[PDB]
Image 1 (cartoon, rainbow over the protein chains, first blue to last red):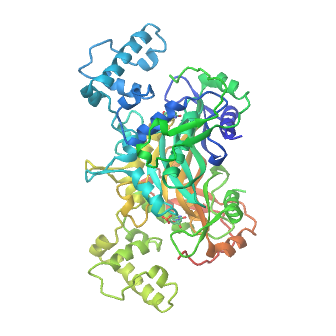
Image 2: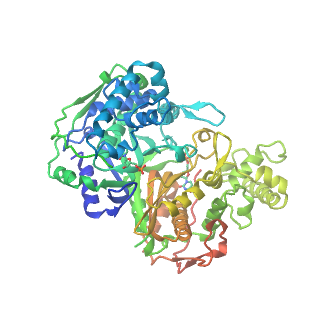
Length: 316
Length: 316
Ligand SMILES: O=c1ccn([C@H]2C[C@H](O)[C@@H](COP(=O)(O)O)O2)c(=O)[nH]1
Ligand SMILES: O=c1ccn([C@H]2C[C@H](O)[C@@H](COP(=O)(O)O)O2)c(=O)[nH]1
């Protein structure tokens, strides 16, 4: 079934990864170097063996696609994926007068008091970003994130390059190009980033009037992260195909470090005992073609009928 | 046997690639997205089913490793891999007074007269680079090539970053890093390069005191190119391991477009009828550890006993 390579990656890490106690005090199982395809003509790979929220994934890809780096657009779709990194900024600023919120990463997952003055300051933070333009401009804006990496990569000559729109125009004029590459990885920023990008670069390819894409993902959370990563790039592959008048081919997912936090063993095992369902179907608005000016309503999921969601603690 | 994944890639493209008539008037068979490992503890992957010149490959990696971008170092080891791109520069300059040498790519492979005034100007060109310092500085120097990408990546703030030496020091201090990445791909240069790099980026990983490396190669000549590419990165993986006091793990080779020019079908088939031999062994100078100051004599191949070389026309 469409999603099986996903369940094969999980199983593979379960009985072959090594214990590697990295970035934290937790531990992981880990493999290095893996690859899996999905034939996108067979259906859209949104995992049916567990409920994944499509709205979150599409509202974030559009954000990237408009080249936007400000959280406000996300909060306006009840998308909180990125609040942490913005709010963190806030928290170490001079204009900040409140509970010291040092290491709320862990601290809001132990202390259950703390973790309530935490959705305190956040709800308060998010709200100001929604309403106060200058605050939004000051702390709502991440700076180095996919949207500006893809569409506004800073040159040294001090201009700004739109890799993604240049590449798309290359696909129309020279589809047989072996050079259709978008990279999110700038070595002059990379050492001072709180998150050097996980999705490092991708490559398009066309043959027989079909578009494929291959993603090199440097580091991957098999349980929480990869389910999302997959639908995100398979969606991009549909948008680009749609804009270039092309058919859709495969999405190829290549990994460097792929891991499973040990706090997730039970949850992944439960999942591995479910039987995939037939995959959902994507539907794009046939009248609109300029994919940079796409809206939520222009992208539809059909026949998604997952098993229930699986709550699981996030990585500390 | 060690080299089999190489023969499996060939076979795979032979009976599954599609005809794609790209960059030229020739044609190729093509697949997109492939991956293969080599367990470097089982021996060094220099193809035994055909004679590959190790001297060429090591003298070029050292060049990259010293961060050098001038051909002269290569010519001093009878390494001509890169003459073309240098000489091309020469040929369109004002100081050039000679036969017009337009499109000597093809032109020296049809005309057999031309192709003799061609090793004329070249032998003449190479010689001046060897002897005339200022000429060497003017036309011997490529500019954007792996050596300066790896070790002298230009910032916009106008400095110069040594990604490779920074990463190596990260491996010593933080081997469990999921961030050990060197990229050769600058989007502000990429559109004005005669050859946007084929070897796009690589990633190191350590576990159980073993070093692995994974290479994302965007575009690959299965017959002429890939045999070299493989020994080049498996060598890098040994050098770095040796410098960091580590054991050697696997070399993982990931491809985007992997192709076979149609002019190579017979030659690859002949090769596929030979039976691999036991692989050779690498030997590094145990006393010297600073790998940036390695010399030819510090790296030895043992027990390489290939089948004969296979002449084949280059791609036009
Ligand atoms: O979309 C995403 C974003 C992040 N990660 C995770 C995996 C790692 O736990 C973390 C990166 O930590 P470092 O890899 O940068 O050390 O990001 C994913 O799997 N998918
Ligand atoms: O070490 C190398 C260098 C080059 N190539 C080839 C494959 C392609 O024929 C060519 C690149 O042409 P474009 O891919 O840039 O279009 O480089 C290799 O396979 N290995």
